[PDB]
Length: 49
DNA sequence: GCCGCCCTGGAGAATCCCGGTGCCGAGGCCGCTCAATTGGTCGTAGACAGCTCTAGCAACCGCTTAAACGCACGTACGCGCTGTCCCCCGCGTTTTAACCGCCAAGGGGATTACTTCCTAGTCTCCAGGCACGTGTCAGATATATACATCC
Image (cartoon, rainbow, N blue to C red; front, side, top):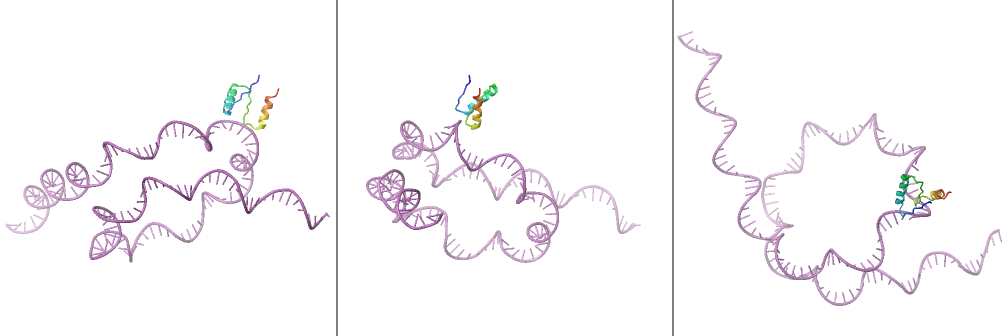
């Protein structure tokens, strides 16, 4: 299964991103700072078979 | 034999040190004396509590778009060097007025004490000016419709 993790603060999302970076898990991120082109890129990267 | 010249010793006067006594600056003491202290009373300034409504704040979003930023070029200006000349500085000499010490009388102004009265504080009562909200009204603006006209 694949998992989404929703959060209210993007700094907590940065904390989980660093946790997965040292942990070494292929992760993707989405927040308000990401522009819509990279949003489309990340959604197509996540939804690919 | 008589007179003139060189060498050396003790007593008179100048100076340093110490003690007694008189004068300047400052502190202890005394006397007045007025303002700080103490004690009591009372009114009210402010602390506290309570309710209502509005602004701020942390952290996030999304969109727009104009400002910020980076880079390349070019050229204008800051800066350094050199010349030049002129004007300010240093010094010697002469003048002159600031400074200090003097009249000569008179008014201005600071105090001390006293008298008086006008005016501003305080209190009570009242009313109208200021703040807020609203109905209404005339000027400004936009369009509806009818008449003259060019192609």
